Length: 141
Image 1 (cartoon, rainbow, N blue to C red):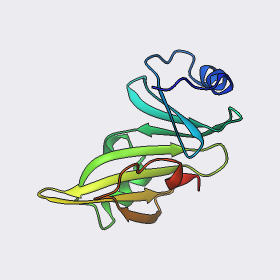
Image 2 (cartoon, rainbow, N blue to C red):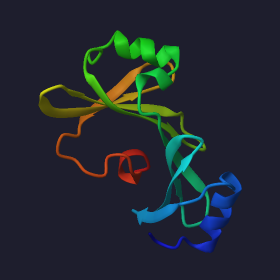
Image 3 (cartoon, one colour):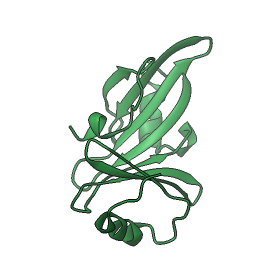
């Protein structure tokens, strides 16, 4: 991967002092650190001032959700869909978002479901033919 700017690396090392195997890239002017920490894959993003802008943690499955978000999922329209991924998205200022990616056995349709921590389904997006679906363009623009 890329070599991050020193100021970005400095902040990252304070957040995640024990991280290893970190793969760095950039998109839309933000820098992303990809790595595993205590059993979970993380993508941690920074701006050019070395300030943390978001962290995305791959929770993988519905068992990792709070009851509140779980209960909302199982009572909503996608309750019986196949869950491909579950991502927790955290920010310095904005409220966290839980992104559940769902599909159906035997068809290629995929949606991202954007839930609040209180279990409100804010919006969904078809991501069947989309790439780069958890970057700055999704959350920071």
